[PDB]
Structures are given as structure tokens and as C-alpha cells.
Image (cartoon, rainbow, N blue to C red; front, side):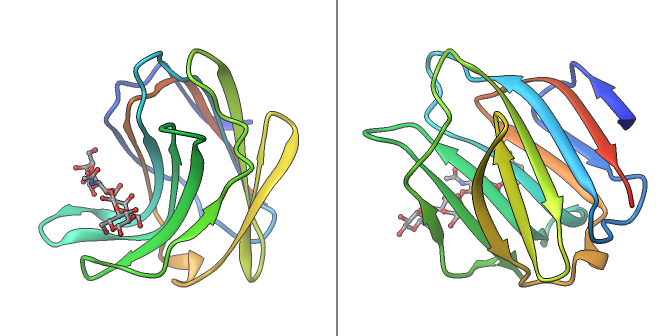
Length: 147
Ligand SMILES: CC(=O)N[C@H]1[C@H](O[C@H]2[C@@H](O)[C@@H](CO)O[C@@H](O[C@H]3[C@H](O)[C@@H](O)[C@H](O)O[C@@H]3CO)[C@@H]2O)O[C@H](CO)[C@@H](O[C@@H]2O[C@H](CO)[C@H](O)[C@H](O)[C@H]2O)[C@@H]1O
């Protein structure tokens, strides 16, 4: 793995140091605290906050009731149609590994070595240069594998 960040402070906002061409991996290892209601990983076009940077891929584990993962895209401060995954591997008080693989037409996400979800590109992945990690989560490491 390349361009590793260890023990970043959350909220984390970081420049992705190369392009997300097909085959590129983003590998995030961390732990979910006991009081977590949600956290999110955002693949952003920049780091503007007003207007809020467009979010090509919002990957949003939620923990209330049975839990789920919500995926969506933010374009000019408007959320698109949510894509919900109900078979969620995340749990409070458990460590995890997220691997986001960039493919031509979509993201593929594996968590803890197991396929979790697909998310079709809504924004060109060439527009992505910024990794945001927010909410109730502890991140141990971030690393990339560029293709
Ligand atoms: C209130 C809140 O937590 N806001 C977050 C924001 O969350 C939204 C996002 O998860 C979308 C995805 O579709 O869903 C929003 O909730 C919807 C419900 O899911 C749905 O059932 C209901 O019908 O409609 C709801 C409203 O649309 C949810 O609020 O996520 C963004 C982007 O990650 C957060 O903004 C980012 O926050 C960080 C700090 O945590 C920084 O400030 C970033 O700059 C900022 O972009 C926002 O806090």
C-alpha cells in the first residue's frame, strides 16, 4: 500500500495523491465506538464547505435498529436517490477493514474480506481528489493502491 496515513484525527479531510483509475484500491482500517449512530466515508470533488463539495460516493454505515449502509451522491448540495444495503457487516465495538475498488462504471466495496456492495458512478471518478471521513469512527490507517 502507498501514501499511508496513520491514526488520523476525525473529522479527516485529505487530498488523494493520485487518480482513481480502474483497479485503484482505497483501504481504510478502523474501529466502531460503542456509542456510534453513524459514520461516513466521502469521495469528494475538492474540500469546499460553502458550497459543500460534491460527493461522488457517500458510504454511510448506520447503526440504529438493525443497521444498514446508505450510499448516495451529492451534487450542488442536493442528495440523489439513496441506495441502501441491509446486509451490513459493521458493528459497534468491532474493528473493520474497508476496501473500495474503483471500476470503470462503479465502485465495488469489500468489508472484512467479503463483498458488500456495488455503487454505479454518478460523477466521473476523475473528479475525485479528496477523502473525507466523518462521524463516530476511529481510523487506524488509510492507504491506496493506484493502477
Ligand atoms: C444530519 C447529518 O448527519 N448530516 C450529514 C449528512 O448526512 C446525510 C446523508 O447521509 C444523506 C445520504 O442520503 O442522508 C441524509 O439523511 C436522509 C435520510 O437518510 C432519509 O431517510 C430522509 O428521508 O432524508 C434525510 C435527509 O436527506 C443525511 O442527513 O452527510 C453529509 C456528508 O457526509 C455531512 O456533511 C459533512 O459533514 C462533515 C462533518 O461530519 C463535514 O462538515 C463535511 O464538510 C460535510 O460535507 C452531514 O453532516
